[PDB]
Length: 218
Length: 222
Image 1 (cartoon, chains in turn brown, cyan):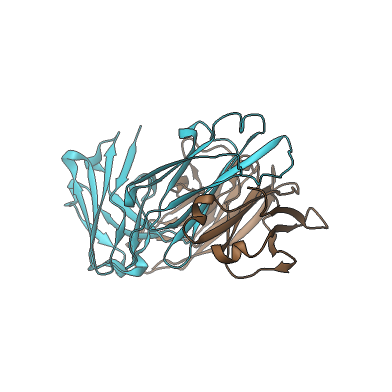
Image 2 (cartoon, chains in turn cyan, red):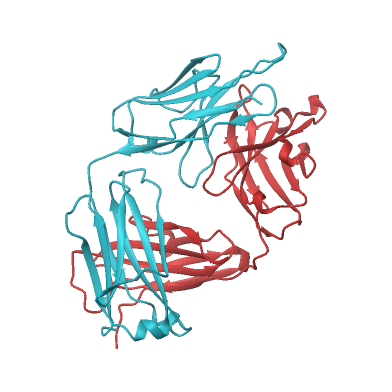
């Protein structure tokens, strides 16, 4: 097998700056060979899109800012200038002798100005309550960088048990991330406590951004 | 123009089988080699196999891990591509893709993907719950609302707001898998003068269980 080693696994670049993604191949045997390279861009919920064919030739439709190069085993993808829509994962591929193989993948973080999360808490729905369970949801939207932390507080106490978190892929238009945290208690213990805090620590702020709700406002 | 429309994906029990289809249109199908590729949730792309042209006797080739279990198949006169996968495994859980072999053994056009889940867990409809701000919350020019889709299997679901009319400040978060059940969430942010004033509804769909729920987001009261 021609086994492709991609590097880096991830990098972060500013709008307009240069991005370089490398791909290595082990060499194979027979003179009856003829093997080629190709690069693919894959965005969030989408099939990968062919960018460059045979190492260095450009594809119809993809902008002048994608270029490829390389000799023998070493191959490179260049993105300059980098634009917000380039936030994706990139794969190299080999096409000659079977099997066709893909590289490990390389994720492009678009580096962009620091930005605070817009956070919002939500009490459990009256409907879920009807069936013995209670979920309290917190939204920490449109922040940068990806790094964030959410602390749940039930009255004056910290609560780590039924906490479920979820992150979006970097946004394609602005370059932000969003997170969602769901604390899932039973109805019984939702009812025997009153104060509900969603506490968000992030780079943009020295003190935790706090949203709360008291159970006494239906 | 050139199109590949995929269908067939769904939950299957381990050791079971499934046939995926890939509907082609916009090019002379009978000339091109076709390919399947898989991609497990949160992982890389892996080659499955190729089926060649009429002129190459419909020759087929597979990545070894599926050598004796998978069959790639072709209907020239109707422009259809098939992948029947026998004796399925937990590891076979993935998004599956068909593609057209373009310029240099490269893959020019790709189908949109179809999810195949292999597990013994049972197919379960979701409970769509509203996320309304707490009654005694102060204003801030804009309000955020949401939906919680909890206790469902398998993926996918689709979430839209007002049938598609709100596509702007939407954040539909990837599902997370607790005890053989997925939990999803979706947030919508609107100008605070178009709610409660105006209608905001989330449209959830879970094709596996034939679920079609809508949820108006209501103010909150005693």
